[PDB]
Image (cartoon, rainbow over all chains, first blue to last red; front, top):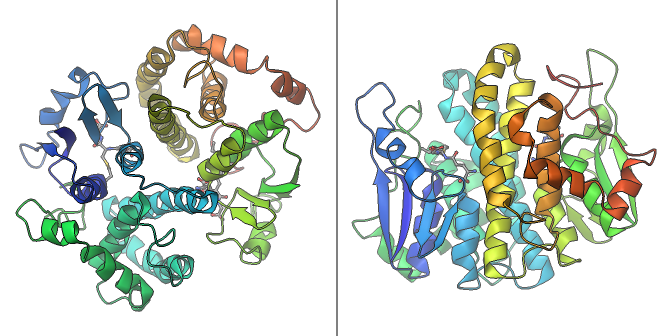
Length: 217
Length: 217
Ligand SMILES: CCCCCCSC[C@H](NC(=O)CC[C@H]([NH3+])C(=O)O)C(=O)NCC(=O)O
Ligand SMILES: CCCCCCSC[C@H](NC(=O)CC[C@H]([NH3+])C(=O)O)C(=O)NCC(=O)O
């Protein structure tokens, strides 16, 4: 079994847990829990961070024999390479590179927001530029089944997480309907994914750590 | 001729310009200029922004015929693949992926400090954490000539830049005296790199936008 370590929260590990589940990778999880509210008690993780033999300790991490990685994108590319779920053609690789990076810029934007004490003050500007961000992704996907072509890749798990989060935030966003929605329905109908979602291991929320103003429940 | 677009400063395009120079790729630059102070109106960019045919409009961007890219790392990979500058084995790909991602974490924590209006009060904590981050990077490299191995990859162009930045913000750092310094010293002695750093187009500053509280022009 491979070991995935991350906080007992959705966050940056969602796409990794889904990929691990789809590619049928035997795994276990180390889900670090919190302690005394409301004082930030990372101790469960902190008591273990500098004793795992990781080169750049962080969350999430994945241990697979002597392979010890940190950096979520790196863990994905690692899992994906064992099942050829990275690009194959040059153009597919460019589409993968550009989106993995772009999806992180949108993930951080959102993260920044739900974390700021000025959330309600920032919410309107954010929603002002959401639609356009979504139109871009819709235009990029076009009529393809997946973000790169007919081949499903790790960037599709990334895209699903990021889009499902935005769907969480604003459930009836016009730009969310259309090819973006069908994409979501396309992802959730994948056999091992459907099965994972109806299992008792799947955690749809909370998206963020307990200190977040939006969705920490 | 590929066209690299970005503001007329060093910023996030440093690693790319060095990779292009070293690879001997013929290129051209579309430097975007900011209006006079304190306005710094960036209309030179927004004017062209949605007229380039880029999927996700942003700076830097790279246009090579029908190839049009916008995320720095993806642009670096695009070039790197053409010259076998990514990893060639599983272990090398892992070092490439983890590093490419950790160095982005490093760069951003630094852009945040230097762009925050609280710089001077944040500066102490940043310095107090630095020696650990440098030591980590030093343990990783070990007695290797390059970060990935005995062959130069694009991640060395990143490490050189993230590190060069730190050398400039705290030259007197002990952590930076060791193999890390031999690495920079080695990077700078490469035929096309040195040939470059002495040219008239080479620019070591400013690292940040004119609005930053540290190093600008
Ligand atoms: C609750 C999730 C909210 C999402 C944003 C914060 S992620 C949490 C944070 N991890 C990181 O910053 C890692 C980022 C890194 N770029 C990666 O991709 O792995 C952590 O707790 N690291 C542990 C540590 O640094 O000790
Ligand atoms: C060492 C870092 C120095 C920082 C200098 C400015 S970074 C560029 C700035 N912000 C970006 O996010 C662009 C970079 C993009 N995120 C990438 O990863 O390639 C921009 O002009 N983006 C274009 C836009 O938003 O219009």
